[PDB]
Image: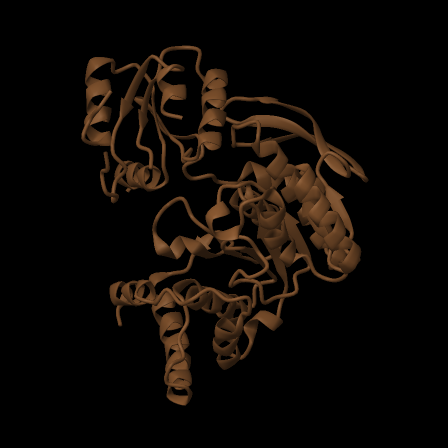
Length: 407
């Protein structure tokens, strides 16, 4: 298969029944030489903040001199972006060969037990572990698909575990209460392995405390063991101070606006430090500083254009958006145009001057109106050229706009 047929092949996998075990992925991983048992890993999960922390952890460790593998849910919708090494998406040619290798193994298996198969995420996940082990990265930062305990990635013993936060976003698949969802996340907490978490809501905190009591895991929690005593807007991003048991790292600078992000940055820092300490690896404040300064955040209050001033954001859920409104008030003091394509609609119309509501690209249109972000964009630029435009609402839109306007 060529690159295109390869990606199509990955998306053709069946929606196999959910189960508590990892037998399917394990059977495939076994046929791949169990690459998940080798090397080092940092396991990350959380309702929100998961990808932000994981990305930051990677940049920090990369700046310290390590080759870091990263398995994530990208905002840019190109498949290759899910598996990276030192933030470089897996090359098309390498994906084609990797897919071929895993397929051959898959076909040998089906030759043994005719009914054998895996889901798409299990296939991709097994392939990711294999890839990282093949390239022999120093460590692979792994983001749980969703939940944790029964997630396809949950087949490793990491150096550190990370639980950013617990919320009801994915309640449909993980549970009706914070406790039930929390029990899924706590599943990535392992015996003797440290766990770094944000300042979890009571029920989530109670579930973690009981879990670490059984695992014996050292528990470092945001706003208890480490925190951010200072944080303020600084140009298109912010300057903040990190503090923990060892002291402070003053005025770090990351190009990521959004008061909520300092919590994910601190989590990342603390996690990187735990990793280094657990592996006798050097990590300096200069390394931390360098990693955050060079970090990149596609679709997060990203100013993809200065003149005209265009901003793209992935704010989708009612919480990620209300937070966005808060960020825009800090960044802009002038009238702006907001183009929104959602899957929160009154919090925008009531917050900003001009607001266009368009459909989300590549999605059914169910039952301020424009037939597309492009029409909304052209109308605003034609009516008021000097007026900044913020495009948000979903994720498919963000990458649609980003891809169209960036290449």
